[PDB]
Length: 183
Ligand SMILES: *[C@@H]1O[C@H](CO)[C@@H](O[C@@H]2O[C@H](CO)[C@@H](O[C@@H]3O[C@H](CO)[C@@H](O)[C@H](O)[C@@H]3O)[C@H](O)[C@H]2NC(C)=O)[C@H](O[C@@H]2O[C@@H](C)[C@@H](O)[C@@H](O)[C@@H]2O)[C@H]1NC(C)=O
Ligand SMILES: [Cu+2]
Ligand SMILES: [Mg+2]
Image: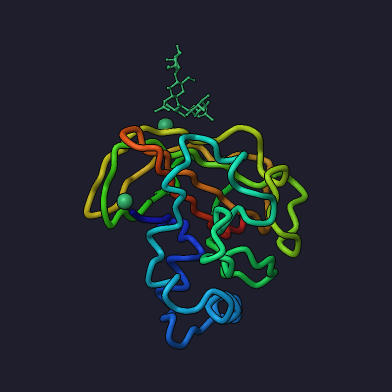
């Protein structure tokens, strides 16, 4: 159980804005759609069944909810999701995935391709084909996994990082969307 902490996922950020009275316009819209309980369950954007079959089980336009109607507020294609500034072509960004319960598993990091439009629902073809980080059981430190990688280098502006956490002792996987701004 968990989600991305840095850059922070939509689901965990909206939780931290308080589901009872959200502060950012995008989270207001998201909580209005999904209701509050989904956001208190920010750590469980999962498919208990995945077994690595992400593209098969998750329809286009439902990447951020992982095809789960419960998390449909995360699929909103808004221009005003709050984004984490991120350098393009750098190896020092402190990536963090907060785990309420650690698991045996690996994390695949994907970024959106050039010419991604935040105003269009996220489709599989909006992401790069290959992950820019794939890491098995990275160090767990103070409740968060610390992950190192090089960000792809010819990027600027509003993008998204999609993190898939596939367990190795279980078919269960977790799915995280993080809004970022390359700069
Ligand atoms: C990201 O990294 C993980 C490993 O940390 C990749 O998963 C592993 O993929 C290996 C092959 O590329 C799998 O091993 C081969 O598996 C079978 C086992 O029966 C053997 O026949 C064969 O000789 C190899 O041993 C390995 O099983 C798999 N590990 C786990 C726990 O699933 C991962 O690959 C991706 O997801 C897996 C589940 C498969 O769908 C892979 O094809 C797929 O590439 C890496 N992800 C990427 C995108 O590269
Ligand atoms: Cu868990
Ligand atoms: Mg690595």
